[PDB]
Length: 177
Image 1 (cartoon, rainbow, N blue to C red):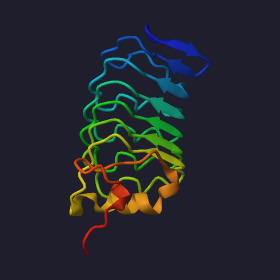
Image 2 (cartoon, helix red, strand yellow):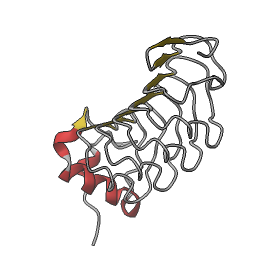
Image 3 (cartoon, rainbow, N blue to C red):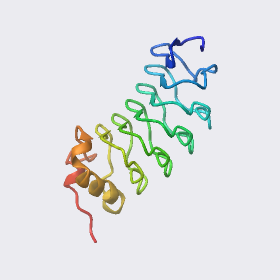
């Protein structure tokens, strides 16, 4: 068990510990990992690669600005992914592609202006998504995939994503073609 964590069974919790980096001794048998309310601002590439049995990963309330490419690729059993209340300015192409079992993905309260096209397409088990409190860029070509995807997957949205500037719903926007 890592120094600032509490390990109960295969559940690893290291919340509100003023952590500045991901703990180094996380066992590979971990099924749940929570690193909430710390001081993380970045993540090393491949940092969670050995945590293949993880069903839940939560990094809410930190100051992460970007994600390493393929940072979630080895976490194929992930059912819950919380990334809200951070400072994300963008998402890597297909970062969620290998998560075919993901049910919950929280991305609210960050600094996202846009997301890559088709970023949620592979999420076949998705039930809930949080996208609110982000300065979405509702200019057209850019917001086209999101407004459309949000409209079709209406029932999964927790809260309501709003356009930066006008405050209008991202789903109220229809792009030109």
